[PDB]
Amino acid sequence: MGRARDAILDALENLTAEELKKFKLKLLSVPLREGYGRIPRGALLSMDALDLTDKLVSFYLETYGAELTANVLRDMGLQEMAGQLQAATHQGSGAAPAGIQAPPQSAAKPGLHFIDQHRAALIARVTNVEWLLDALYGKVLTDEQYQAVRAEPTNPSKMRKLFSFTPAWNWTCKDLLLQALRESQSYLVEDLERS
């Protein structure tokens, strides 16, 4: 019993003997969320579709086990068995044929105002808004990016975007701004650090 338990068994039993081996290495190659524990490939080669099926349920839980799998088969190009596996664990009626497509690549941030509360806080306390922007000029941001930020309409908007360039800030980048803030006033370094 267990539609999800049957879901895993069905997908693995459908892969070819050699294609099945790929699913094993795919688990050791796909990055995991926290870290749980990667099952050694040999342990999987020793177990069979049934024995390993019961194990994905014991170690990776029943649902989280099939969910993680639907993503692997999706990488193998078996979108048909993958869409079927997720459905086996939850048919979910009302599902339209095709048109929803994948959500936008832009991670929709929560509509809860809070992360911006520290931007306006320091911008209003820094006063010299240009002092920090001019500091990162030619340093971390390129000449075209720094200008795109200065082309903003509002003045505080120039800083808000600069902070959104997080994917461009490295460990040294963050220290670059935190350091310039101490040179002008150590108080903000502590007030902003003690979030």
Image (cartoon, grey):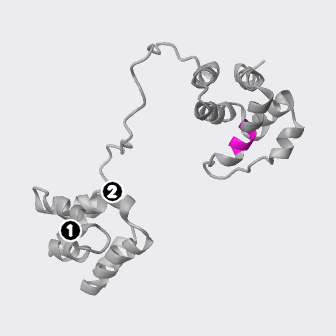
Q: Is residue 6 above or below residue 155?
A: above
Q: Amino acid at mark 2?
A: Ile
Q: Is residue 5 left or right of residue 125?
A: right
Q: Which residue is most to the front?
A: 18
Q: Residues within 10 Å of mark 2 (few under 14, many from 20)?
A: few
Q: Which residue is at 29% across, 67% downward?
A: 141
Q: Amino acid at mark 1?
A: Ile
Please state the extent of the stretch shown in magenta in the rendering. 23-27
Residue 79 screen position, x and y as percent: 57, 25
Q: Earlier in the sequence, mark 2 or mark 1?
A: 2
Q: Do the residues under discs 2 and 1 have CB atoms within 8 angstroms? A: no
Question: How many angstroms separate mark 2 from mark 1 (CA)?
Answer: 13 Å
Residue 76 screen position, x and y as percent: 62, 32
Q: Is residue 120 magenta?
A: no
Q: Is residue 92 left or right of residue 172?
A: right
- Residue 139 position by quadrant: bottom left
Q: Is residue 192 left or right of residue 33?
A: left
Q: Is residue 106 above or below residue 140?
A: above
Q: Is residue 112 above or below residue 18?
A: below
Q: Which residue is mark 2?
A: 115
Secondary structure at badge 1 equals helix
Q: Quadrant of the C terminus?
A: bottom left
Q: Which residue is at 17% across, 58% downward?
A: 157
- Residue 127 position by quadrant: bottom left
Q: Residues within 10 Å of mark 1 (few under 14, many from 20)?
A: some
Q: Quadrant of the N terminus?
A: top right
Secondary structure at badge 2 equals loop
Q: Which residue is mark 1?
A: 123
Residue 143 screen position, x and y as percent: 22, 67
SS majority, magenta? helix
